[PDB]
Image 1 (cartoon, chains in turn blue, cyan):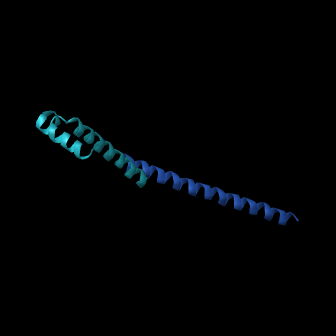
Image 2 (tube, helix red, strand yellow; image 1 turned 90 degrees about the horizontal axis):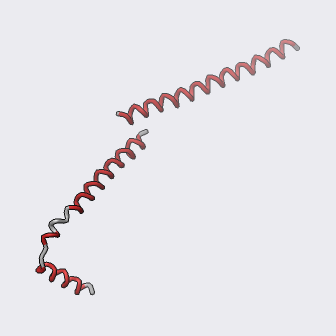
Image 3 (cartoon, rainbow over the protein chains, first blue to last red; image 1 turned 90 degrees about the vertical axis):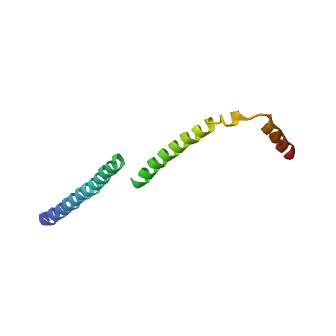
Length: 43
Length: 50
């Protein structure tokens, strides 16, 4: 019972870690596209 | 970003051609050279359009 509860609690950690990688990838792509946009508009 | 580049550029072209068209109307001094011989022509075409 201890081993099965430890496995479900580790599975939730793996899903939340990949969700934080998901939010970092989409927000850095938005920020990089915005900075290249202000570069072309100032140019 | 490319749509905002073209919209900024079009606002500049519209402002430049708006001030050039506002400068060409203000040069009406050629029309200030007129006499009664062209006024008789203008009153003739004002007769023709009733």
